[PDB]
Image 1 (spheres, rainbow over the protein chains, first blue to last red):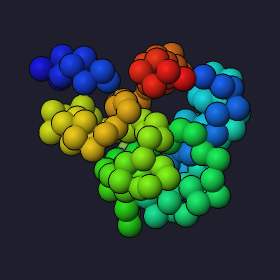
Image 2: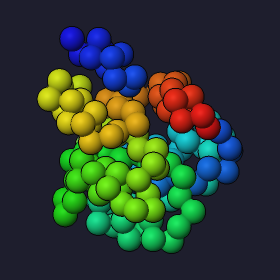
Image 3: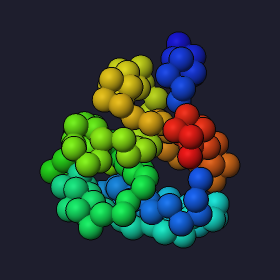
Amino acid sequence: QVDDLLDSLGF
Amino acid sequence: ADKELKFLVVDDFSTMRRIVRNLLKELGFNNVEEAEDGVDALNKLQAGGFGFIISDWNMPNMDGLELLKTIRADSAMSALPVLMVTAEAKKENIIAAAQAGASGYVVKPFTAATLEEKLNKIFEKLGM
Ligand code: BEF
Ligand SMILES: [Mg+2]
């Protein structure tokens, strides 16, 4: 949910 | 992106600014100035010509989130790239950065390789 949330954001 | 892109590195710890500036240099970005908090940053930005901001989150007077929101809502500076730096990737903090318009988000400490990766992601999205 962290590295995966980052991906979603293009971060 | 252009090697002469002018960066402002914002952090209340002088050693962290020196480190980021040194990493930028390692990547070929030599045009770098420093600011010690969000108020100092906005002062220095009035000089014009800045093309990229790298900002810490926790700073006195004006923090990095407050700085980012101000830049994003500013008539002249609204599209400036801003790479936000934090001490720990927490969901709440990442989501705040997203809502405010952070161009990128990186957790300290990081390598030049990580910095280049994050800068390149921003350049690609912005067509720089
Ligand atoms: F003070 Be910063 F958020 F590392
Ligand atoms: Mg700080």
